[PDB]
Length: 15
Length: 76
Length: 125
Length: 69
Image (tube, rainbow over all chains, first blue to last red; front, top):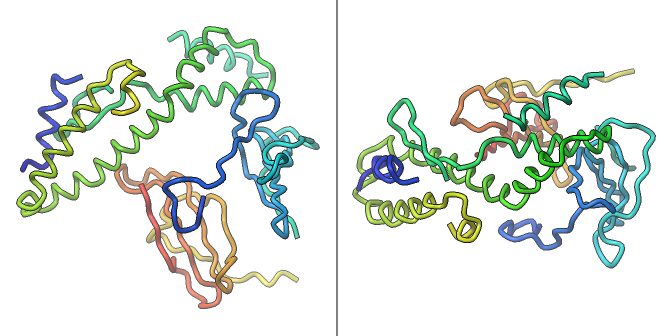
């Protein structure tokens, strides 16, 4: 559903 | 590669001389009449004679008359 | 005789990831550094004059020799993902038709991001 | 004599882009192609744009524009 903020969630503390 | 399909190369061969280093090409060319004797301009001159099919495929021999990388080359 | 630049080479070597941005666009990032081109330049320098570049530098080049095309493909995936995420950011009705596909693709993207210095599962990711 | 023809200079897709290797019309009649080097005139925009023109049609704008990533 989200455009790009899903990657903002899977890159903040993902590594 | 093939002209239409470009998701897998048909005849992908290496351009390496006796050294194991990947010879970075620089403005190579193809011979006239499609005799597959393509001449590779290395990272600094080194005119390479090469073929594409049979055991002659790949790097055959080098020769120089210069040191810097080859800029232009064709046939007629 | 720019031998000091050749000394600078040794000094330069003697010197997936993730980082922030400006427009709150957490782009996909590669764990490596843009040094593969410099390693190729080192190879050119070696065949060019026969420098006695440190063996540690040559071995770092060999270390990157087994994982650099993977990194170049990663950089291409990053840039093409940017190329199309901007297109998705353009309109708003795109989500209504791409939502499930977006979730399934982004989950695998995060799984690909999960690689951190691991040549074993680096390639399938 | 040097019968200097025209010059395909149209910045719509040739804006500060360095020309990479050229290619004559090996299939077309005098409709060449020019590969382009990395140009950072815009970050997300394509670096090099393969443009083809037409000598047989006597123009300046790129006939066929191709910009990959």
